[PDB]
Amino acid sequence: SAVKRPAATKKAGQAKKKKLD
Amino acid sequence: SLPAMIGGVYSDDNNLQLEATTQFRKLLSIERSPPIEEVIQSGVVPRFVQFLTREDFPQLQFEAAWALTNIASGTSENTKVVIDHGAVPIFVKLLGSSSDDVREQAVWALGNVAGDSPKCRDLVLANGALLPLLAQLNEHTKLSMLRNATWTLSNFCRGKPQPSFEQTRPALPALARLIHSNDEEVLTDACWALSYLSDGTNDKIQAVIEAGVCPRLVELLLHPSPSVLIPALRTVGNIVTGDDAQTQCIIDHQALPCLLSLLTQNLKKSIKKEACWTISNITAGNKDQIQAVINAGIIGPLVNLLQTAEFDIKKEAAWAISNATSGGSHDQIKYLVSEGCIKPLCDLLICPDIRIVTVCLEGLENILKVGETDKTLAAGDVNVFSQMIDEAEGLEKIENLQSHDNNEIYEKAVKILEAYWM
Image: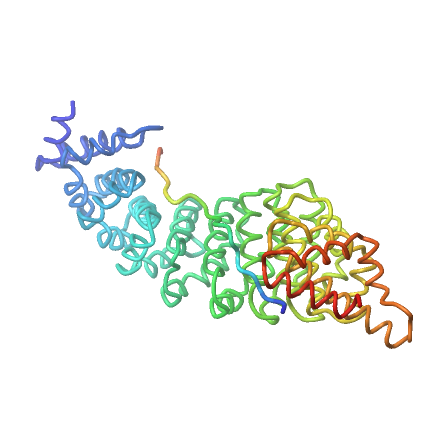
């Protein structure tokens, strides 16, 4: 060892946005 | 009402067309529950797509681009209708319009199509949306355009499986410039895009690092807004999953004292968990990188988290302390012991997570070899660290791990007991 560990939880912003004005 | 709007968009009079496209837009621009399904069933979508190509009438173009943006903001079935009427190549073309309003709406529309799924994201990039999107990014770019384009850019990078690296590589210089903005919205979306590009193989992390992002990403660890901090921390954490040289890029810019402040502030459990995961990928590196963790004063508060925190934090803190025992020098391992690491590693031996049991067992074994070296060199009667493990109630736990179902945990316990307690 030691081994590098990638992120195991999904973290992301907003996929879509509606324009109100 | 509606049969006059359909007749208007389907009429050949410029003023009738603009009137009903504004009416359809307003109806689609409503707060919650827009009648996207009813606007589609009225057969007006192909007319709006035709109204996009009307470069002699920019007002209708913008109204038609805004109505399609809101249709594309609905369900996947609504986004597909926009795609089926050939809007994607027309919106890419509208990125080169004399109207700033049309260019900005085309950018939003593409972001909404690219946001739907990796398939739709791939269709937008295949239609060559990336280069013209980056072309309307300079020093004279308005804030509203900077926000719309930075959010669209994040959607171009978003999703699993990730986009081809050659396909998102032109974005990296622009994203490195956008993280220098003081606008929290731009920062949030540029950090999101960089957290996606850095989430993968070391060739990806290498290109992110060569764009010069590491100093500004470390600064962003101290941003007061969690909206910025969350993708900032995730980006920093993804970069340090690379080789020692790649990880060094982050450490050289005083990230370790910044990462410590996230552990000692009254912050969300998920922020502390991510800081601990980041630190663990640094203690997974060379002796100089572990030294920098020690030098920053992280070991003390890390040992306390390993002992007292919530299980998800204790998990990452376990990997952080164990990694340090794996790559660390004899005197560094002893510093870990003097900061009180044996007891909390022992206490997690009866933990139901087999991965964590294995991590704490490896950490205790690495410590034991060091304790043995001290005994041999000084011709002592006993291994000082084997005494400490017994005092912490760790010995009875290792003896009980001989009954564990898991072979790797069983074989480890036997190997440890034979080499140090016979």
